[PDB]
Length: 489
Ligand SMILES: [Ca+2]
Figure 1 (cartoon, protein in one colour):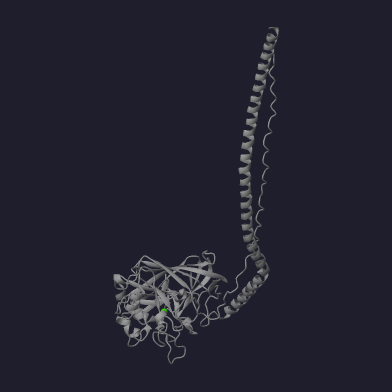
Figure 2: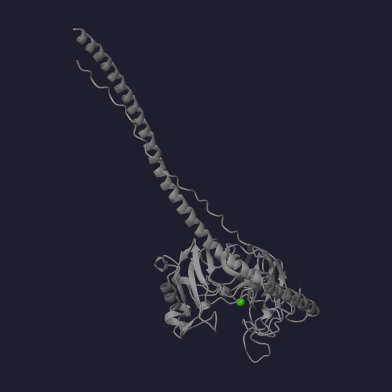
C-alpha cells in the first residue's frame, strides 16, 4: 500500500508536468504559425512588389530610349542649323543691303512710266502655283463637272465649244440653275483630262482646272489652297491660303444666280458670271474677297506692307472693271491708266481698250500699233492697266467686279468714242485674280529669309531605376521539449 501511495503521488506529478509541457508546446506552435503567416505575407508582397519594380524600370527605360530617339534627331537638326546660321544670315543681310540700294536708285525714276510712284520692294512672291490643290466649302451649290460641260456645249458658248475652246465669258449660266446640276461635292473641269488639248480664255500657255459653284447674293465659297510650291513672304515659305469669295449683294445683275469658277491655281483667281445670254444695261457683278496666307506651321502670316497686284482693270466705252472696299493703301504706277477715285481703283480718267479711243494710250489687244496687247501677264506695259495695294496684317480683303459705266458716273462725264454708245449693255461677268505679280518695272524682290537663332534641345532626364528587394527567409521550426516518462510501481 505504501508503494501504491508513493506511485500515485509520482503519477500525479507526471500528469501535471506532462500537461505543462504540452500547453507550452501548443503556445510555442501558435507563435510559430503566426510567424509563418507574417513571413508569407511579407514575401507575397515582396514578390508582387519586385515584379512591379521590374515593370517600372522597363517602362522608364523604354520611355527614356524614346526620348533619346527624338533628342538625337532634334540635336542633329540643331547642330546643322547652327552651322548654317551665319551663311543664311549673310545672304539675308546681303540682299537687304542690295534692296536698300536699289530702292535709293528707284527714287530717281518714280515718276517715269511703269514705275511705282512710291518705291517699294515686293516681299511677297506669289505668281505661279500650277500644282496647287483646292478644297472648297460653300453655303451655295456645288456644280457637277458634267453639268458645266453641258452648259459650255449649249447656247452662247457652243460655237467656241465645237472648236475645242472653252470661252468662259460666253457661258450662259441659264443651264447651270437646275437641281440636276448640283453635285455632292466639288468637281473639277477645264482643259485637262479628256480636254487636255483644248484652249480656254483664261490662259494660253497652260492647262487650267476649276471647281464650280452656283451662288446667290450674300452666299459664298471658301477656298483652301495647299501644296503651294513657289510662293514666299520675306523668303519664308507660304504653305496654305484660305480665300473666301462672296457675291456682293449690291451687284446689279439681273436674276438671282451667279456661277463661280475657282481655279486650282490660286494665282489664276476666279471667273464670276451672271450672264444669261444677253447683255444688260445698268448691270454689275462684284465679288468680295477675304484672304489669309499661312506659313509652314499653319500660322497666319502677318503682312508688313506686302504688295498685292491689282491688274487687268479693263475699261471700255460702256464698262468699268474696278476694285473697292479694300484693306491697305493703293499705290499708283506712274503712267498707268489706273488710279484711285472715291475709294475705287480703276481707269479713272480714260478708257484703256483701244489707242485713240477715250484717251487710251495703247490697245489692250495685239495689233499693228506699238505697245498694243498691254493686257497680258507678259506684256512689258501690262502696268498700263494695273496698280497695287500695300497691305499689312493677317486678314485682308478687297472687292473686285465689272459694272456698266452709267452706274459710276453720268454720261456727261464720260469719254466719247465716235460711233459708240456709252449706254450699251454689257455681260455681267468677269475674270480676275489677286496675286503678287506686280506689273511695275524693276521692283526689288525679297528671296532670302532671315534665319532665326537655333534653339538647342534638352537632353532627356535620366531614367530613375529602383532595385528589387531580397525575399524573406522562412521561420525556423521551434524545438519542442520532450515529454516526461510515466512512472512505474
Ligand atoms: Ca481684266
